[PDB]
Image 1 (cartoon, rainbow, N blue to C red):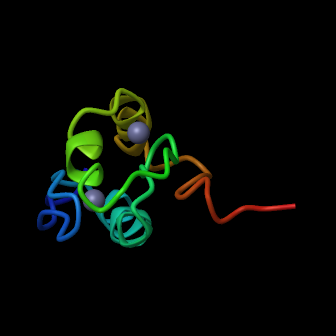
Image 2: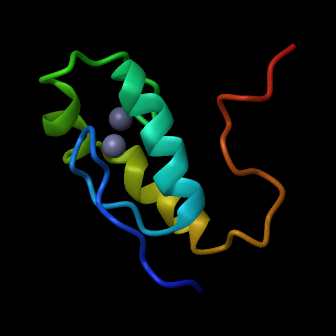
Length: 77
Ligand SMILES: [Zn+2]
Ligand SMILES: [Zn+2]
């Protein structure tokens, strides 16, 4: 584990770790869920990133950050 970083400056959903926190600064800047890529609005963003259930699944995956994946939105083909 690592020391918990600052709150997301875009959706206000507190990130657990640095990977989750950067990913957030990235998808919230485009109002897309960090976890389900729901393509929110700038006022749907805070309410949805606060309530998404895929958030918990991906973030329980970030507790096992030792794995290969970080941001499943950057790998494309
Ligand atoms: Zn955010
Ligand atoms: Zn979501």
